[PDB]
Length: 62
Image 1 (cartoon, rainbow, N blue to C red):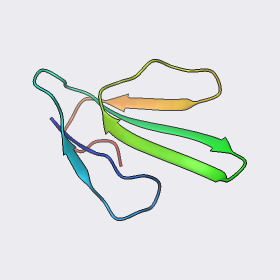
Image 2: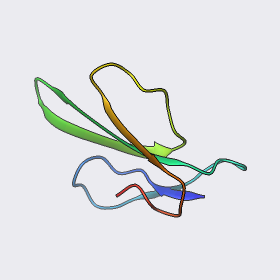
Image 3: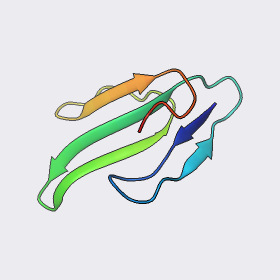
Image 4: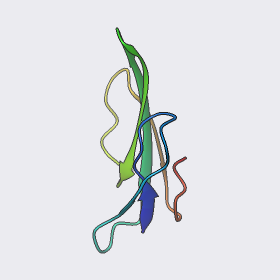
């Protein structure tokens, strides 16, 4: 699996996941600085206040 791993609207970058990892994620939240989007391999735990979206296809997390 290859997923996007760039933050917010920055130039696109990808990451090759570890073997057997089939998911990618897109996490979004707000802090005092602004709205942040983080992307990477896997499907992390749902945390309070954080918006998380997981998908299971190549570069699915734009």
